[PDB]
Image (spheres, coloured by chain):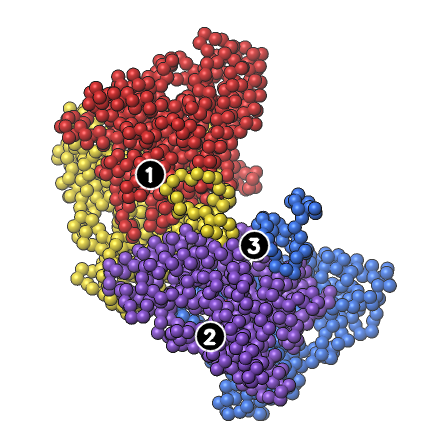
Chain colours: A yellow, B red, C purple, D blue
Amino acid sequence: LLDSRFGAKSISTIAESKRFPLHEMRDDVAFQIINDELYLDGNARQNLATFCQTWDDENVHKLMDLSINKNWIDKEEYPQSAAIDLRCVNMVADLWHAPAPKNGQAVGTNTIGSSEACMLGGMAMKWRWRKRMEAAGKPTDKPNLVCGPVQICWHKFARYWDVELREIPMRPGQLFMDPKRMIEACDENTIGVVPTFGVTYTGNYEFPQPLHDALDKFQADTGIDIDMHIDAASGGFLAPFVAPDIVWDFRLPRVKSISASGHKFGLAPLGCGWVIWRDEEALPQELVFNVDYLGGQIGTFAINFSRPAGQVIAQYYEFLRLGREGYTKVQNASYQVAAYLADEIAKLGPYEFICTGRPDEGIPAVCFKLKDGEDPGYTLYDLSERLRLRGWQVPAFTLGGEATDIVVMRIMCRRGFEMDFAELLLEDYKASLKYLSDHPKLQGIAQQNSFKHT
Amino acid sequence: LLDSRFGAKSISTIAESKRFPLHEMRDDVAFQIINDELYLDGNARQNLATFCQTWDDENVHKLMDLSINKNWIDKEEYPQSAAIDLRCVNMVADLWHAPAPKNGQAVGTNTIGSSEACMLGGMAMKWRWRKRMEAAGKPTDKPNLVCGPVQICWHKFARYWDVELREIPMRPGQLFMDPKRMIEACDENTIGVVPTFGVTYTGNYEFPQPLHDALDKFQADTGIDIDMHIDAASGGFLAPFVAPDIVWDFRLPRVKSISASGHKFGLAPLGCGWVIWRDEEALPQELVFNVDYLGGQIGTFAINFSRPAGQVIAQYYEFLRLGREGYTKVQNASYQVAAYLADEIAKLGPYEFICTGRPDEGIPAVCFKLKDGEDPGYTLYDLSERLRLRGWQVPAFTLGGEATDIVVMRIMCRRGFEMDFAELLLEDYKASLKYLSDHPKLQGIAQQNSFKHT
Amino acid sequence: KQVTDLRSELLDSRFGAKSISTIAESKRFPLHEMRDDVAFQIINDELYLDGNARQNLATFCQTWDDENVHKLMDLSINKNWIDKEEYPQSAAIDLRCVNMVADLWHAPAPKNGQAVGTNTIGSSEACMLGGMAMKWRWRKRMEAAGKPTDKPNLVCGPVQICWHKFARYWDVELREIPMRPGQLFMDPKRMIEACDENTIGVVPTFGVTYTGNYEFPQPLHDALDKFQADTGIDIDMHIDAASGGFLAPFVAPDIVWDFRLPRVKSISASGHKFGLAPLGCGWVIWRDEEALPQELVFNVDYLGGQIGTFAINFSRPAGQVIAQYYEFLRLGREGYTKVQNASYQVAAYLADEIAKLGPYEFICTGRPDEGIPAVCFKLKDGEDPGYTLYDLSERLRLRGWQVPAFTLGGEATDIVVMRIMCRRGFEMDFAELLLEDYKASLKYLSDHPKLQGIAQQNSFKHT
Amino acid sequence: ELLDSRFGAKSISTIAESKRFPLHEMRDDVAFQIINDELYLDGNARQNLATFCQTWDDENVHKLMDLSINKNWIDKEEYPQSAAIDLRCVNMVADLWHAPAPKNGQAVGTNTIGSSEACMLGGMAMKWRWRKRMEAAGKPTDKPNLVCGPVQICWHKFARYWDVELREIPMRPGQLFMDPKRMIEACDENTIGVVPTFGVTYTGNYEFPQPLHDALDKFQADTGIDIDMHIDAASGGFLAPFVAPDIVWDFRLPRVKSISASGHKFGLAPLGCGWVIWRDEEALPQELVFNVDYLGGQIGTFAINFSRPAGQVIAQYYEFLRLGREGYTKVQNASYQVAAYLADEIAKLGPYEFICTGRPDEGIPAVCFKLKDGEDPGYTLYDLSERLRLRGWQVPAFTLGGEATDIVVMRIMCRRGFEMDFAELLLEDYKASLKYLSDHPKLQGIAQQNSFKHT
Ligand SMILES: Cc1ncc(COP(=O)(O)O)c(C)c1O
Ligand SMILES: Cc1ncc(COP(=O)(O)O)c(C)c1O
Ligand SMILES: Cc1ncc(COP(=O)(O)O)c(C)c1O
Ligand SMILES: Cc1ncc(COP(=O)(O)O)c(C)c1O
């Protein structure tokens, strides 16, 4: 066998792909082989399912390229990267109205993503709860966590750390965690409540303030003092700029910690998350580990150890070049696209909207389902497939709880998906509808849910 | 205030370094500002403390640059990256003699580094142990883990997952976990034993074979069946090439899982780890989460979620271009440098070596201390400072346990630190000794341990 | 009660500034200037909507990427092919290429020092030039015989659209032998039935666009010899070797289709196809000076003497010619043979593997002696696997592949075929992946019977 | 035996076996370096003042072209966005030339490789429209002719390739262009159309369509013969719309059925871009349009070429977007200022008669002059041209055709990149050349070879 690229004896990556290669290969050949098959990956420009950054900025490529070997954990060898990281933590803390540091540094850390950030927040929540119950002479064998339609990372947290997950079910007419059902699930064993400030499946905000009021009333009626951790994976970098009046952060006494994804609306490249604590008291010191350096010793609360510092640096770049002024315009642009799509899509079929891209209701997303008892001659799964033939990935999937019978389509509007592209989407959307109308036999055939976790 | 680079009003990164920036800034100015202060970071070429890759390969830079937005978790949009990842898992499994897969795919996963890989391995160990104790209706709230001079990630595991850490103390003449002391620490609550195949502090291997025999005798005498997880962060990509005869992997029945760092001797860029399980039985399905995609559901056992796929791609590039043939030559080269330094350094002072860079004893490292009761006229702390003035970072620190009075110097030889550089280090080493000899007052002044964790 | 902080103007999320739409007023010439880098990023971003064709198995055009070719093209962006004066070296390289192509096709040794031929933008222009020369030669004959040159016709088989254009644009009656069950190509018998005194020439297609098969000029050549013997009518040929011209000379030297045949007066082929050159390169060679009527050649003055030219286009980039030369130099016969063979191996593999998956009748199986590296098949007559090739094609698109399904012409206007093209870059590993997706598609069609018959639109087949 | 000093290895000659297809292969990086090194023998054209084609370098254009190397212009299916951008360009150029508003929203026209193909297409459409008006009237369609002035060679090629009698009004002292009177004298019932050249290749002057249009209206009034026009605005098409909007030469004139122009000339696009627009659907005989199938339905195409790169269209769009009318006006005016400056400055150096002085109202940014009849300054423009070449400049000296055969002119083209600073350097070298010819009289009359003048 020969290879038409190299004009020589073929080298297959498939052949013995299950055994460690025995011989050396020319470097440039290995590179070209891998480079060529990476073309099979999509570029996500037409993928409207993910929240993760997919746009390309030359300066970010340069900063990442320069940081390939900078080790985030090695404060000693990379002092400047460590300094930039500390600045970011303070800036994010400031953004969320965290109390002014009693020293000079906010309590928090950078992470690989919201998953780790949530685990750290969850562990701290569990430890604070354990300390309290112990100080009351009560048991700590059956901890539980109250939440709404959370992302899979919380299911993982509950499973990995043995905490009963009390997830309020999504239901027709009540898809999110409301004050009433939240309280019904709370007790002395509840380590905390986790509102999701930007639900993954729909894009809506679960508002912490009303929930906070209910928890105040709860402590008043029972003496049970319950705190909150806000999972603001997406909303944490949206509301502070486009909807400052929504009180969801550290302005609320019970909010002990907050986490968010830098690689989502934080605009950072893949591999960046943040978790901030209200103050030192909010973070049990037993979870922090002190490691020595020539410059002294620094404490860290992290699951990972060695890793690249490039994303942190790129995140700092976004903070510096944009500021509140810049983020407000960037985020607003996405909301305008989402709002436009929602209004335009509503004129094309019998739809019921769950999220319409309004800044006061959630993130830049459009989420809808077909109206109950309405048959346009296709399902959202069918429409989703027609759109794929046009290059778009618009996820169609079912909701959980008793809403398992609810099929929705969610469209995410992130940086790069400008108004001109949304108009193209609408063109293909209409073309797909006409095709489905001209070929009725297509209805009901497609029935596989698309990736919806991120 | 003006800036001499831009010839315009000064823009400080320190002034408002604790608040989120208010205004926008020209993108390129923000880039140059950050680019300029990153020069304050070292390049680590003269840093002989870390195990992490610090050499630069143009092809790796290109692959990483192309992968900046490729999401490791999104199998749907990046199918080829996911396929390459699967190949790597199988190749690493093959490298460690894992039993041939039933379905065709080995059981394991890529990780951010060895920390995450060890957590996963640790959780699986805890779960397998629990499933046994639970069947016998015994308490499962006081699990313990037996190990030697482990890296900090195991202390974190113990703390975060409430497992008693039974670390055999480092002591004069017995710095590692031996069969006798290991058994003395084992009981029905031991979830497993963790040998460190390449101790972080010294570079020596803890040999699993003798420990394995002791565990066989243990089960024979008590009925208690204890398994092992090999922390081969560094050794996992060394012995298979330069010392195939050392039996430390899956060839041993009790070894249920193994973890290693790709960004160490695996030659991958920062942000790559690996953990492999012997077979399906070794990994409790309760820990695996299944997520749906268009092409079907894929299960995952990971702490992190969204993150970049570049390192895995880069790792595959190393596997392809080198093979066993290439890795053997690369690792041998490092061992030759280490062996050379050990031999040469021994001629310069009254030293007792703990590791001399021998392939059959450990990793490419040199570790020594001053002979007991010997006073050359300086401490290794003093020598370390002298070498810093020459641009080298050669860590001097104390050991734990009873060897708390012992101060050692550890030199790590990784790719890029060639024979010519070792010669220069020897020159500076001699120069340092002469200076210390001509300036006696320096003795005893330096007393701060250097970063030793990685 | 408001809680937001909004701006009252459409914004762009990339630039954090007022939005600039390319769709708004995209029907009027822009009025104002715009920052250069912004215009660049705006265009760069929408170009991501284009496919990269790596998974497109319909085209014959080069889609692989070679760094050196990128550099040569980048350096030649302003080099004008027609300006021999300012770009002497590009002109020299072009002359070398003409000679090398002429040599490759066994053209008679130049009666001076340079072969008769020219580079073109593609096979279309090359064919037009060959067609005009053919018409002119024929006209000169009839006029010498005192006959009317009022009704010229051209005999051919299932030619590519460029010949339909030539016939239309130069008023030549196109006598295309119909594609039919049992015989989809131009055979000697039907060819002769279409020939007469007004036939300007015959155009065999050495690598049919629609199927990939070669129309063999030798048997046709014999028939034309017999024809002149029985009627005195002397008819010549122009070989449309768009794809085959850079295949057979390397993997099947024994096939006599070129200038080795007396009647072959000119040949054309595409450099940007199997010639391996980047888009925008074609070639047409004539047997000798006599084969090219000087009335079609235009002489322009240059600072160092006047050079003759026979082309439709004038000013244009010389980069593709340079890149073509680079392929000739780095590969040679030795290299082209290996590159082409690699594609044949992939095609042959797919044909053999695909045959095991359904009731198919193959028209082309990627054999070097029969045609180009392509696989062409249809469902066996009176066989119903539970899907049409159109349905299969759509399922493959959902997996990212573009495998064209379309109908044949003539009496085969009712037959639907699927054609797979194997060009440089589509290596064995990718063919395996295609097979995996092919099988997955079949299982899906099997589990979802309602899909059968829904898809009914032909894919782009002309190139 | 023979070695190469670059590779320190056996020599690899491109001259040896340069007429025979190479037999063996060689290292790719060696093949690249060998070709890269001889390409240095090509000029960079920065000092070439003969061509109209773009020669300046813009980094963004290099990037767009590099990204487009494999984008196939004809493959609408695989490259949808490239096709969309192309449609926008057609509409924008149509709007630029005042084409009537489309009935369906899309203007009638197409991108081409250059003005040559654009002119062929325009010419075929002209021939077809004339033929049909003829067949519908039951007349003979076998003797067509085309009336024009000092046309570029592409029209001679069209005439020859499509069997149309070319009636070119001869260039003559005093009246080097096609005037209304001589145009009419050449028109008849077999005239498929008139082709004014809005920017004559040889001189740079505009042939004004308006006066010719009036004569054609009177012609139809007196004879009933209705003749249309195709404007060859290869260079002028991207000049007058910005610096001289008041000149009526485009679709504002009823008889102008089609217009063609070069994007790679003053359109500022890279080599390989042309444009041809038709007034409306009726102006383009559908018999010439071919419809091909593709998943999205079917698209009609009228072009001689088929597969080709879409990079130039994309680059052309980039110029349209970044400049707009505002930008083009400033860019074009800058070239006119240089031309006007050179004309006025050169006039002070010798006994010259100017035929083009770079005035926006008269033509393109070019300077064209000849020596005053009988004035012998002691050299010919051929001699001057050679002296300028020794200083690195290529300033073409050549003879006019028709009845202007005795005339030797020098033409200077001012395109983007040739700024005022460079013009001053040219003037310095021009003066130095004059002084040298003055001090070395024996040089007079020696040079006598015309330079490339077609493009
Ligand atoms: C609410 C929410 N939390 C957590 C995550 C996981 O974040 P990451 O992928 O960065 O771990 C997501 C995607 C999310 O939408
Ligand atoms: C034995 C050992 N285990 C684990 C680690 C941590 O690995 P990582 O920094 O890649 O998480 C190190 C550095 C080590 O030396
Ligand atoms: C047989 C045949 N001839 C001519 C052409 C046209 O070639 P080009 O697109 O290069 O003009 C093609 C595509 C073809 O397949
Ligand atoms: C008036 C005129 N028409 C046509 C052309 C031919 O243009 P192209 O070289 O771009 O085919 C030129 C150079 C010209 O000056």
Give the label on residue D217, or none. Answer: none
Where is residue B17 drawn, in percent x and y? 43, 35
Residue nearest the viewer, comparing D345 with D61: D61
Residue for badge 1 = B109
Could you classify mark 1 by the number of other residues whose Cα lies within 10 Å: few (under 14), some (14-19), or many (20 or more)?
A: many
Q: Label 1 lies in what chain?
A: B
Q: Can I make out residue C183 in this image?
A: yes
Task: For the residues labelled 2 and 1, say whether their Cβ atoms are less than 8 Å apart.
Answer: no
- Residue C437 location, quadrant: bottom left
Foreground disc of the pair 3, 1: 3
Question: Which three-letter amino acid code belongs to the residue tagged 1?
Answer: Thr
Question: Which three-letter amino acid code belongs to the residue tagged 2?
Answer: Met
- Residue B305 location, quadrant: top left
Ligand 3 neighbours mark 3 (CB distance < 8 Å) = no
Give the label on residue C334, or none. Answer: 3
- Mark found first going from the N terminus, 2 or 3: 2
Residue at 53 percent across and 15 percent down: it is B347
Where is residue B122 drawn, in percent x and y? 28, 30
Q: Is residue D173 left or right of residue B354?
A: right
Q: Is residue C317 left or right of residue D170?
A: left
Residue nearest the viewer, comparing D44 with C228: C228
Give the label on residue C186, or none. Answer: 2
Check chain identity for marks 3 and 1: say if they share one. no
Residue at 13 percent across and 35 percent down: it is A221
- Residue C320 location, quadrant: bottom right
Question: Which three-letter amino acid code belongs to the residue tagged 3?
Answer: Glu
Could you classify mark 3 by the number of other residues whose Cα lies within 10 Å: few (under 14), some (14-19), or many (20 or more)?
A: some
Ligand 3 neighbours mark 2 (CB distance < 8 Å) = no
